[PDB]
Image (cartoon, rainbow over the protein chains, first blue to last red):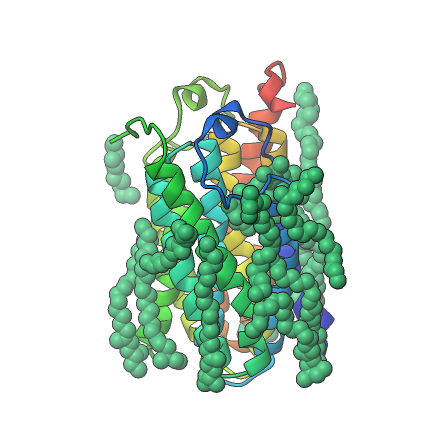
Length: 157
Length: 156
Ligand SMILES: C=CC1=C(C)c2cc3[nH]c(cc4nc(cc5[nH]c(cc1n2)c(C)c5C=C)C(C)=C4CCC(=O)O)c(CCC(=O)O)c3C
Ligand SMILES: CCCCCC/C=C/CCCCCCCCCC(=O)O[C@H](CO)COC(=O)CCCCCCCCCCCCCCC
Ligand SMILES: CCCCCCCC/C=C/CCCCCCCC(=O)OC[C@H](O)CO
Ligand SMILES: CCCCCCCC/C=C/CCCCCCCC(=O)OC[C@H](O)CO
Ligand SMILES: CCCCCCCC/C=C/CCCCCCCC(=O)OC[C@H](O)CO
Ligand SMILES: CCCCCCCC/C=C/CCCCCCCC(=O)OC[C@H](O)CO
Ligand SMILES: CCCCCCCC/C=C/CCCCCCCC(=O)OC[C@H](O)CO
Ligand SMILES: CCCCCCCC/C=C/CCCCCCCC(=O)OC[C@H](O)CO
Ligand SMILES: CCCCCCCC/C=C/CCCCCCCC(=O)OC[C@H](O)CO
Ligand SMILES: CCCCCCCC/C=C\CCCCCCCC(=O)OC[C@H](O)CO
Ligand SMILES: CCCCCCCC/C=C\CCCCCCCC(=O)OC[C@H](O)CO
């Protein structure tokens, strides 16, 4: 087991894709106007939390990718990352709060699955995913309360 | 041989970019863009991407069973994420120049995945060849969309 920079940088570069979804966000009166739960973090917290999570999830995947039988785990990892990438444009760009809730719940499921499969192969890789599952849980809660606490207009059928 | 749990996991992962296409059907904005002469008709695209989701998932299923496939699957994760990113940037936000950067990075990781797949399993490499071809065409379309509509602010 090693600090493998080819692996680590590949997984980190892959995080550049969800990172870009956040980068292309702007101040948005729609978002500012939303009713929010008391425990909602300020806007500046989210890029810092996500950057930390990108590094942790990449290091976890780096460890696992060096182990025999890691195929299912990395398939879950690929799914987790793609739904993560999908969520921000659906919620912030398309303003489809209901569809975004479906997306983040699928994300949550593949984050949980990835974490479970990582623990099966390597404890530290599983542990690194725990703050990710926790943040994903909070993020789902925010999407849900956003839906519950506000006016929602119909999406396209 | 055939590992259904693996294949279905990879196929499910394709549900994410497949969803971007479902939620962002080509705009009246898109139809009014100046198109390069070789632009395919609209029905070609969901045909192409649906086929590619099945081919790339088949390829990944084969590779994920093999020893030493970690770097290959890391590339696969990378290309899928940038694939998922591209449609919302181009069709959603209509930032054509940013989208070009995204699809070029996508292209690189599709090429890297293909190469990596070939080192481990010839058939998985072959399944990625039409993907690299299509990503090349997509990159060209995105480049031409800019070049041919440079008077639009969203092209620059
Ligand atoms: C005040 C300005 C910004 C706010 C509130 C912001 C908030 C968010 N950014 C998100 C996505 C993101 N923003 C991110 C980095 C950035 N974030 C940026 C600007 C902002 N991004 C810029 C600019 C970034 C580029 C460095 C990243 C990296 C993500 C990716 C989230 C994900 O799903 O991976 C998400 C979705 C996930 C969640 O709810 O936990 C929120 C809420
Ligand atoms: C949008 C930001 C994403 C970064 C864009 C850079 C992507 C370039 C594509 C790389 C293709 C790899 C080359 C394939 C052929 C090499 C031979 C081979 O395929 O086999 C080599 C031998 O194992 C593999 O070498 C490598 O692993 C090189 C890949 C390194 C990945 C790029 C790292 C970029 C640094 C990350 C910076 C931070 C990112 C943002 C943080 C959120
Ligand atoms: C919302 C975010 C909340 C969490 C924020 C945390 C802030 C970052 C601190 C953690 C450092 C973790 C270190 C992880 C690096 C260890 C893995 C690794 O380096 O492995 C090396 C190689 O595998 C040989 O063992
Ligand atoms: C050992 C110490 C470790 C330190 C490592 C670096 C920490 C970087 C982030 C700090 C804040 C993290 C939690 C942020 C909670 C924000 C709550 C809030 O709303 O504060 C807004 C602020 O008051 C507006 O002026
Ligand atoms: C379950 C609690 C998780 C919630 C807390 C979230 C904060 C970030 C946690 C990261 C754990 C890793 C940090 C400690 C560094 C690990 C050292 C390492 O992994 O080294 C491997 C090798 O076996 C020896 O060096
Ligand atoms: C407002 C929302 C705030 C956040 C809400 C809280 C989120 C709860 C998440 C749970 C993470 C706990 C996961 C712990 C799983 C550990 C599994 C384990 O350790 O299994 C190891 C074993 O060796 C295998 O073989
Ligand atoms: C166009 C792309 C759209 C994407 C849509 C893709 C949806 C795929 C998910 C199916 C879940 C079905 C769950 C069935 C899981 C069965 C697992 C299994 O039985 O595996 C056996 C194992 O391989 C024995 O060794
Ligand atoms: C288009 C809308 C989005 C569509 C997306 C559908 C989301 C549901 C995902 C499918 C289930 C994936 C099936 C994977 C089951 C594998 C379970 C498994 O293999 O367990 C691990 C194994 O035991 C240890 O190696
Ligand atoms: C490792 C990272 C490598 C990948 C990063 C690649 C980034 C390239 C991005 C392009 C920005 C836009 C510049 C492209 C301009 C093409 C359109 C053009 O301007 O056409 C000429 C004129 O506008 C018509 O008359
Ligand atoms: C288990 C290790 C942690 C894993 C998960 C990492 C999550 C921590 C990251 C940032 C949260 C800080 C933001 C918290 C700010 C809450 C919003 C707030 O400021 O509300 C104040 C209210 O008025 C009275 O509490
Ligand atoms: C515009 C730029 C155009 C560039 C387009 C090319 C990009 C990919 C380069 C190499 C492909 C070949 C990858 C295979 C490398 C050797 C594979 C080998 O091991 O053999 C394969 C198979 O398993 C039995 O031959």
